[PDB]
Amino acid sequence: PNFSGNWKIIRSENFEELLKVLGVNVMLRKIAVAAASKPAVEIKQEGDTFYIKTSTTVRTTEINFKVGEEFEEQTVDGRPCKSLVKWESENKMVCEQKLLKGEGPKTSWTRELTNDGELILTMTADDVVCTKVFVRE
């Protein structure tokens, strides 16, 4: 699979609820939802090595990881975590997250490519699942 490119969002389902079960207050959820309505996602993939930059109106996040190697990032609610990505199948990577400090709902994410060239991002927090779908610019 080849994830490299600049990606634009085309579908988003259940993002507010994801924040809500992570205990994010109404004010910040409403802001966050609007801020993330038209993000910029840049991915540079070199084999199993990934650079992913996600930008909203007010936030920018850059992660750098290799599949199979632990790295640090933040949960969707902004808590620092140790993450580990594995390939579940050819075109689909799954990430388990462990908080660096404290405890909280179990969070994870997945990214996968479809034959039609869509990138599907799933984020979970306990039993709440948020799906976002992107296409290349």
Image: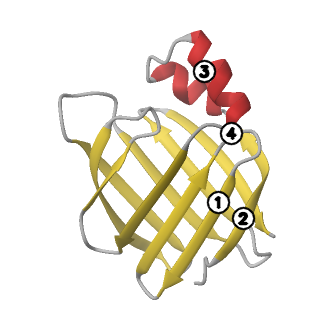
Q: Considering the numbered disc 4 on the image, is that residue within a helix, a strand or a loop?
A: loop
| Neighbour tally class for label 4: few under 14, some 14-19, many 20 plus, Cα within 10 Å | some
Whether residues under marks 2 and 1 lie with C-beta atoms below 8 angstroms apart, the answer is: yes
From this viewpoint, which residue is outermost toward the bottom?
A: 47
Tag 3 or tag 2, which sits nearer the N-term? 2
Marking on residue 41: 1
Amino acid type of the residue tagged 2 in the rendering: Trp
Mark 3 touches mark 4? (CB < 8 Å): no
Which residue matches tag 2?
Answer: 7
Other-residue count near label 3 (Cα within 10 Å), few / some / many at <14 / 14–19 / ≥20: some
Given the image, on which type of amino acid does mark 3 rest?
Arg
| Quarter placement of the N terminus | bottom right
Dot 3: what SS?
helix
* Residue designated by label 3: 29
Q: Residue 57 carries which label?
A: 4
Cα gap from disc 3 to disc 4, whole angstroms? 14 Å
Q: Which amino acid does label 1 sit on?
A: Val
User: Quick one: label 1 or label 3, which is nearer the N terminus?
Assistant: 3
Residue at screen point 61% across, 76% down: 3
- Disc 1 crowd rating (10 Å Cα; few below 14, some 14-19, many 20+) is many
